[PDB]
Image 1 (cartoon, rainbow, N blue to C red):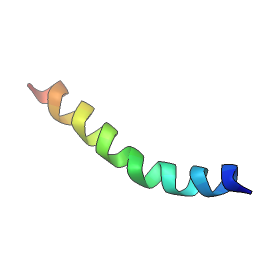
Image 2: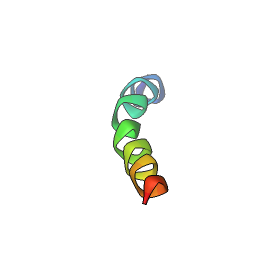
Image 3: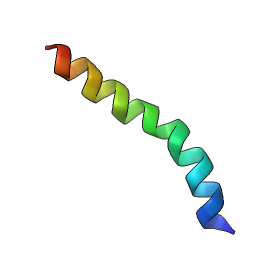
Length: 27
């Protein structure tokens, strides 16, 4: 069930991308 594992860890790693977009939006 690799798809389920990738869903759990993907939301965690996604914070890097979301944080980058939040930072550039302020600039």
